[PDB]
Image (cartoon, rainbow, N blue to C red):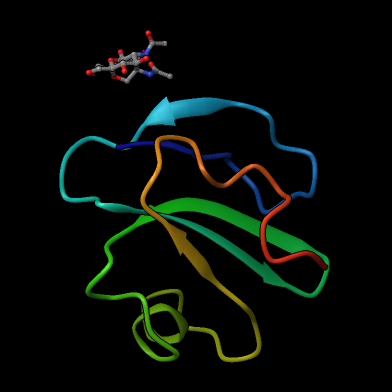
Length: 77
Ligand SMILES: *[C@@H]1O[C@H](CO)[C@@H](O[C@@H]2O[C@H](CO)[C@@H](O)[C@H](O)[C@H]2NC(C)=O)[C@H](O)[C@H]1NC(C)=O
């Protein structure tokens, strides 16, 4: 399950990379103008398992089951 992972929440990250094991759902969150592109599990794909791990509250999140599915262009702005 490959997934994108940048060192900062920017809206122009085009670097793909394997997210090791422990990941079955790419995650593309967009809390306003910050785009969080990190790998995530499907069991934790809810409106709380992602707002608690990141320690945040206002934000979005779309899980994907395809290698490199988070490329800034799935749920729209
Ligand atoms: C992530 O690791 C995989 C190893 O599985 C690299 O190779 C991919 O292997 C799968 C099948 O297991 C193929 O379907 C992919 O097309 C392969 N990817 C490539 C680029 O050949 C994969 O390349 C690795 N990704 C990165 C960014 O390193």
